Amino acid sequence: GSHMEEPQSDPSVEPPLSQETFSDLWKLLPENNVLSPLPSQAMDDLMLSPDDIEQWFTEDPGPDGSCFNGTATGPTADPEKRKLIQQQLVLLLHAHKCQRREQANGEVRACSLPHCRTMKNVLNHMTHCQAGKACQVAHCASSRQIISHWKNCTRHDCPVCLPLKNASDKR
Ligand SMILES: [Zn+2]
Ligand SMILES: [Zn+2]
Ligand SMILES: [Zn+2]
């Protein structure tokens, strides 16, 4: 053929994603990234409001632990709760890459998708924010729990990390 498969088939040149990539991604990412999730393949059909993020990554309801349907009727360990983390986390990637695509090409305009518009505003605040999980903006505080997952998790076999590492196979 006209080219070789070595950059994808040989471990001496293959440049795959690292566990620290997702931690820097939402802060300092360059305008030439290739992980950009497209609406034709992204599970955006499973979308939520920023307040429901607190149902899969828990925040205290009060000092007495006053339980609710989101913890007592349908616990955080349910398989459907994991789908909601995966689909929302993949959109934090889209919202950081979509804003960069417009910076790289002034002839086009960013998404009309309210979830993309929501997350790109949160990411541009969260990079300068100092309270994080304690921030008084519900959208900032909720997104910081998602960012805190990749910062503390180091496993290969995790219901959130495994499908992301499988999708980010940039060999
Ligand atoms: Zn977008
Ligand atoms: Zn904040
Ligand atoms: Zn994990």
Image (tube, helix red, strand yellow):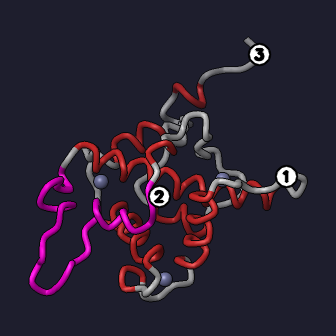
- The amino acid sitting under disc 1 is Val
Which residue, given by chain and number where applicable, does mark 2 sit on?
A: 22
Q: How crowded is mark 3: few (under 14 residues within 10 Å), some or many (20 or more)?
A: few
The residue shown at (62%, 40%) is: 38
User: Ligand 3 falls in which quarter?
Assistant: bottom left
Q: Which mark is residue 2?
A: 3
Task: Locate residue 29: give its quadrant.
Answer: bottom right
Magenta stretch contains residue 79:
no
Whether pointer 1 and pointer 2 mark residues with C-beta atoms closer than 8 Å, the reply is: no
Q: Which type of secondary structure does the marked residue at label 3 adopt?
A: loop
Would you call the spot at circle 2 few (<14 residues within 10 Å), some (14-19), or many (20 or more)?
some
Q: Which residues make up the magenta segment?
A: 48-77
In this rendering, would 113 be left or right of 11?
right
Q: Where is residue 36 in the image (x, y as percent from the top left)?
A: 62, 46
Q: Residue 108 carries which label?
A: 1
Can you say which quadrant of the picture contains the C terminus? top right
Q: Which of marks 3 and 2 is nearer the N terminus?
A: 3
Q: What amino acid does circle 3 point to?
A: Ser
Front tag of 1 and 2:
1
Q: Which residue lies furthest to the left in this view?
A: 64
Residue 72 within the magenta-colored segment of the rendering: yes
The majority secondary structure of the magenta stretch comes to loop
Q: Residue at x 28, y 44 (%)?
A: 80
Q: Where is residue 66 in the image (x, y as percent from the top left)?
A: 12, 77
The numbered mark at residue 87 is none
The residue depicted at 38 percent of the width and 64 percent of the height is: 146
Q: Residue at x 52, y 58 (%)?
A: 92
Q: Is residue 121 left or right of residue 137?
A: right
- Which is in the foreground here, disc 1 or disc 3? 1
Q: Which of 149 and 63 is in front in this view?
A: 63
